[PDB]
Amino acid sequence: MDKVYLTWWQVDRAIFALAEKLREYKPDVIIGVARGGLIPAVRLSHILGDIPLKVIDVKFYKGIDERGEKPVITIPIHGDLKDKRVVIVDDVSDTGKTLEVVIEEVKKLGAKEIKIACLAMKPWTSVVPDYYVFRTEKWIVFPWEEFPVIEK
Amino acid sequence: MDKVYLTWWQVDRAIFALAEKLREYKPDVIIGVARGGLIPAVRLSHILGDIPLKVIDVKFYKRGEKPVITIPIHGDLKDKRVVIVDDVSDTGKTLEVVIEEVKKLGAKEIKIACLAMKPWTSVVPDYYVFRTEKWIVFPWEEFPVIEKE
Amino acid sequence: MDKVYLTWWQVDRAIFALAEKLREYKPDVIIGVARGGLIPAVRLSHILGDIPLKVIDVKFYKGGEKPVITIPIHGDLKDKRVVIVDDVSDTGKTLEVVIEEVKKLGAKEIKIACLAMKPWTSVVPDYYVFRTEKWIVFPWEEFPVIEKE
Amino acid sequence: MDKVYLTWWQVDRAIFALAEKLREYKPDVIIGVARGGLIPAVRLSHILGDIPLKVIDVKFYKGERGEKPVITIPIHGDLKDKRVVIVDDVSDTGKTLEVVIEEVKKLGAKEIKIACLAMKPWTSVVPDYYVFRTEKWIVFPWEEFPVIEKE
Amino acid sequence: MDKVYLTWWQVDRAIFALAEKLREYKPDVIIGVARGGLIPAVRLSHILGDIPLKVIDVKFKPVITIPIHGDLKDKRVVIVDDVSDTGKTLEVVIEEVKKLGAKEIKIACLAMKPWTSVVPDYYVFRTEKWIVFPWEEFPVIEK
Amino acid sequence: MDKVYLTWWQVDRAIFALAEKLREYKPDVIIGVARGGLIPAVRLSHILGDIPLKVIDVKFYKGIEKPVITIPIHGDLKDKRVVIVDDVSDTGKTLEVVIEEVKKLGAKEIKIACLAMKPWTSVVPDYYVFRTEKWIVFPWEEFPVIEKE
Amino acid sequence: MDKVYLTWWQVDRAIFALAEKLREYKPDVIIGVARGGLIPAVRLSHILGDIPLKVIDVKFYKGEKPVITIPIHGDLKDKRVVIVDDVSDTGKTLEVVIEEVKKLGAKEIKIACLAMKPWTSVVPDYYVFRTEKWIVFPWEEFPVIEK
Amino acid sequence: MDKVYLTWWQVDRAIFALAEKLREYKPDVIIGVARGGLIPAVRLSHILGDIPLKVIDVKFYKGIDGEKPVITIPIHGDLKDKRVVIVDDVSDTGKTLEVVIEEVKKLGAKEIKIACLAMKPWTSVVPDYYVFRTEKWIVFPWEEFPVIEK
Amino acid sequence: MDKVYLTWWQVDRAIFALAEKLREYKPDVIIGVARGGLIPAVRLSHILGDIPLKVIDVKFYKGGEKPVITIPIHGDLKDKRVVIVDDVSDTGKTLEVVIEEVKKLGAKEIKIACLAMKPWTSVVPDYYVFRTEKWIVFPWEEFPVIEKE
Amino acid sequence: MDKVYLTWWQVDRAIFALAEKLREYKPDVIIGVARGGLIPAVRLSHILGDIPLKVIDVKFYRGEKPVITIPIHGDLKDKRVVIVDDVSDTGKTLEVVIEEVKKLGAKEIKIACLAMKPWTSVVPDYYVFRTEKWIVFPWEEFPVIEK
Amino acid sequence: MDKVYLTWWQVDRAIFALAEKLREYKPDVIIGVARGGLIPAVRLSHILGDIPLKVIDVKFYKEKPVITIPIHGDLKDKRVVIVDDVSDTGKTLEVVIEEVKKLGAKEIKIACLAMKPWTSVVPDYYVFRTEKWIVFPWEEFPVIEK
Amino acid sequence: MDKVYLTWWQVDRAIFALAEKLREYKPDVIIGVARGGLIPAVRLSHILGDIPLKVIDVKFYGEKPVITIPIHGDLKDKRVVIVDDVSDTGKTLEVVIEEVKKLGAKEIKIACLAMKPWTSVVPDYYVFRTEKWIVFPWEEFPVIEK
């Protein structure tokens, strides 16, 4: 087993730890990255005084290039975030691909300050989270994810 | 006790059970109600074969309470079989706002699935697992603390 | 069961118990919110020395929702010790409107008495007997019948 | 014991009986006459498909503050084009029902009907619908008892 | 108010009273006379060790709306009715029970009036007024 | 029917009536006269701030009637306001035996509260609610059965 | 509590409530499932217009098999029937009655019960109380736990 | 709800049921326990053939701060060759009943039997006869309906 | 709520508790009824010293309704102390069969152990933990879903 | 059911919720009542900033009398104390502890519990669960009913 | 710690995944191999429309296999599915396949939660692949004494 | 992830396993080592027939030991068992053993959930072995910032 299976208690404790740290930052709004992002996002929305939750969904297709992928925003976020402390919540920063796209949609809305929180991150990511709990190189199977079946 | 504190497992086993019954329905799109609907919708979305996911947020503001659409449903739903997902149908006040909002978009067929439902609701879910009148604390919600006064 | 069916006696004994504690407060006026509060207001009114009885009716219409005063209360209660009587404090929405209307009559001190209250209400009664989350059918209400859809 | 002590089950049954006769009349609004008149008026409001309830309070004072019938709680909104039913616990002399009847007409009531739990042989206002007849004083389920002290 | 309005607590205590007296008799079966009679019949049925219950309905002339079958041969019977007013119905019931050859026959009622032609073997209330039972509805007086 | 059958609601409302008068008296202890007497005694005990309850049982024998105390009053009653409670004062014979037993325990003051009284009783209660000449069947009493001779 | 002890008054109010709904159905006949359904039937009979009252009694003896101790008399052809029982728990007694009522060929069939348990195989058409707990009806004897 | 409010009727019916099961026992004396079982004992006494009624009252006094039990209303004489029935309203913790039992045993009861209307699972004294079973707060008909104030 | 959803851990703690009490009984063989008792019996099998595990499956078919032993017990249980393991003793019909069936194999002593039991069962387990009248959904069963008929 | 069986996760979420409120009270010391309050005290201790931890064990043995098996060590003069326990049932154990804490001159005292029963004489300043049922906590052994 | 400790949520999720593949196969009967096998067997039994469940137990003595809990009845024209916790050597699974064939199994499929790479019986469906010993949620632990 | 995250179910089973071994020993009293050690100690206190529990708390800042919560009473003629979560260096357990001897403990046994290879004090009963930092079910997690 070269995969990491995070339990729900591991995710709850991780979220509680992040919360205490995000309290010093005082977020005005949360932006959850779908789909895994929305678990920590919803919980943080509650734990931090029911602060507004915005949802964004970024998806990737192969497009007209073989070596390359262009982002298609499934679920957008609206309204402006001028003078608003923003905190983007996602489950893990693997390549940082999705996060970079999200940081650009948050700036287009005039985000005052921007912080990034994740449950875990991988060493090579191009977007290190400002706050995270787990560090690993393996593939992470979260408590809310199903398992693949191996057939002959 | 005064409240029901649903564990992640109990909610997960309910999402699976709900998914099994929703296969027969074959949803084209899943509409999750913010915020209690989100987690369940995420899991059902993938279990049902990575079907498209949409979000809708309804807040009520105070004489009298008027509903506000925090996050509107993007795109249209013409000819699509829709499924509105929520954690619980309590009064059915939010669900009724969603139902109409989906109808504006052109859902071929609308179906509602909830983890729980309360006997006195005005919107009986087409699919639900838990039934109670008690105060329900879902795993993603904060455990309320009672203080003095 | 799914509902609590309070018998006339259980309610009579609660009204008696509430009067016993309301003596110390020495009410000058009793505001019974119809319709659930009227029968209890009538009895407390007499037990407490035949004190003046006023009535208020608040109805909530749908089309958001705004409250409409079906039966308004009049006459200033300047420096009068008022007691608001109702059958139950459920969400607290009605009792909040009744409080606003009593204060509009210049009420000195306001106390609230109910036979029952639900743990999630916004207006906890200064006096109550029954505490539950279940569906409450008071003796004066009709016993609901469940019919197939 | 020269008094008639009505149980809640007698009051409940008397109310279900009045409901059946009242369905035929198809009341549009109920006017409850305080105080004991509210118990029956409320119950009928529910049984008859939640028809709107209005309250009227009539008080006959005697010896300060008194001259003739005073209307403690008035009824408002016109009843123009409405079938009205006036509910009270008992029509003893009818002094009260008469004043109420006058306030209703004074509001334009399309038609008027009277229903009570009981009535006494000497009333000047015989209810269109009622259940008990007696000359004794009635102690309803919702009333307290006086105590007899030596003195 | 020239009527007697029995409460459920009066009816319940009447039954418990009857039951203790009926235990000395040891009924093998109970014959309940619809309609008001079923109430006491049912209660005595459970109270007396869940003994068999047969329902007989007599309407008036005399036509049996609900017949009782089987033979009460060598079976001590107790006929349960709410009130023995004139005795008319009860006398008809006494027949059908003998026709089935009952080892013995006893009658138990809640009430009974002075003039009845059939005095119950066991009863509780005696009156001359009309009895309105807990399970009955009330008439309305109109103009 | 030549008997008066008192319901529990009649008995409760009587006891509540008696209680409000006994509050002006502020009794220190209650002497409940078994057996029927024990129902209103226990209730008044609870209604008047759990004031202590003592029990007394008086039986009569064919006087060659002579009284016999089955259950005596424990302790003494020096400097305490007393209230003797019974269901009904019929002849007054029982109450008289009790008034005497109370006095010889040195009761400061003495009061008598009954549910009912009959016109010819020798001991008129200081407080009562029902007056009748008929035999009274209380809510806690069973009925006799009329068999054939 | 372990059990539910319905009072005469509660039962009576349920009956009045059921009757109000049953009016729209205009029953031609009422069949009281004995013994529990009898008392409710009697009242429903008078309340709906002194409509005919038939009685049925199905006893289960021990696998197991039913024994109709008191069969329904006459035929119900072209008649709208209403079966009345105190509670629909398992539903085994009612199913044996729905059939027996079809034999006599009934026009329409609706079931009216005071109570109903969630796991019942026979969800009545009209009911008031809903519980999973042990129900003790007024006419039944209060159970006593001994050692 | 938070509490169970038994009606007089529910209590009367339970008393009848207990009486019926007690008939086989054939009690000689009924020892009502104050204050809860007084009313039930009064009724049981008559129903079971006017058998003599005795009363015992046990109170707990807090020392100057535990709790010590003291007999407020004693039982005179003895209970030799007498089949007894101790009647109470409910057997919650069983503390009271245990004291009443020791006293009854000291008076030489031939046989003892406990009968209560209610019983709580965690009790140290399971009644020999009982009807209601719950863990909730029980308000008997003879008690005051509790009011909650701020 | 309307149903009880025992978690794996709750069931596990129950099994450990039962195992501890059985240690005194020293069971020779464990008989799990299918399918509810299988999982519990496996754990108790190992915990109690890797004692042999036999299986029995009783199903009920309608016409009346009688039992059919889908999986009989293998071997004989002479002079052995037996322990029947089941998830819940609801009505007791299933266990009654299993008992006769085990008695046929001539068991020295028979003992019943379940996780749960209902008040009305005709077969009170010798060892149980949970007690309820509600619908019990064990971890191995599926979470029922309610759909609109 | 007859008893409530709180899971480790439910207790842990209660403790996390409780800690958030206790943050506003700025405790100086935590007194964990044995044995039930020890586990929640340990965790609360750490979460609130490793604030010192005292332990007290009160047992009950003519009549019933409280005995302190483990006394609090040190003094609490001027300290803002927090007494931690699993459940406030009757309230008799918490009463003895409040007295013992005062004997050490505690300035402010607060009581934090996971659960509380409605008839308790010591209503907690902070609690999560409310019920009258028999509460089995994760650390207690599941009770087995035998014959 | 050299062992793999599997949680109940892992076992449940693995079972739900297996069941979704087994629906395409539409089994008629499930054969759970005692003892650990009965866990997933019982669960799949319910998940797949309560299809019948037979139990088989294979022990070994010196090796020579002995069936301690035989499965009776026939599987003629019945797509069978054998369920177990883990396929290690495959030793036991082979003895089970033989017994299933000896009863007329129309088709045979094997579903396991896990499998070691060196097994002689690679399951048609499995979820976990490991070389370490696996401790399942229903298993007790050894105490290292002195 | 170079840390080991124990679950409550792993701890519960560890505790149950240890408990069966401790029944052979029959402890008179248990000595829980705060703080993580209280979890096992309380649990064992209950499982082993509610035997008396005592709490001790040692702290360090060379590295001098500071007893934050002492124990008292004579453990004369009493078989004692010290319970801790993990025996890493053996540092705390040496102090605790000292405190128990000063009370004249008849026999002393040590029981931990886990232990590490280099410990100066090897538990008489333990379940897990590791060289990694163990994160218990009741502990919080550190957050990594920039």
Image: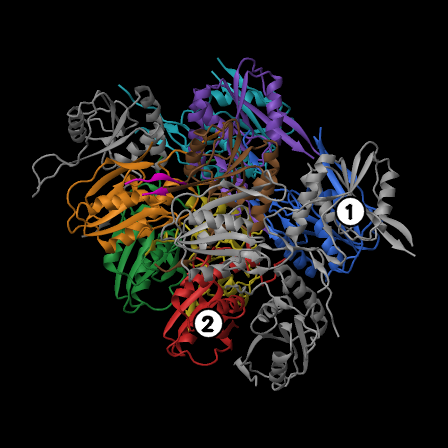
Chain colours: B brown, C orange, E cyan, F green, G purple, H yellow, I blue, J red
Residue C13, image x and y in percent?
Answer: 35, 47
Q: Secondary structure at mark 2?
A: strand
Residue C73: percent from left, percent from top: 20, 40
Residue contact at pointers 1 and 2, CB within 8 angstroms: no
Circle 2 marks a residue in which chain? Answer: J
Percent position (x, y) of residue B92?
A: 43, 37
- Is residue B64 covered in magenta? yes
Q: Position of residue G129 (x, y in %)?
A: 48, 36
Is C88 placed left or right of E16 in the picture? left
Q: Residues within 10 Å of mark 2 (few under 14, many from 20)?
A: many
Give the residue type that dot 1 points to: Val
- Mark 1 chain: I
Q: Which residue is mark 2?
A: J30
Residue I144 in view in this figure: no
Region rendered in magenta: B60-70
Q: Quarter holding the C terminus of chain B?
A: bottom left
- Which of J69 and B133 lies nearest the eye of the viewer? B133
User: Please, what secondary structure does the residue beneath circle 1 have?
Assistant: strand
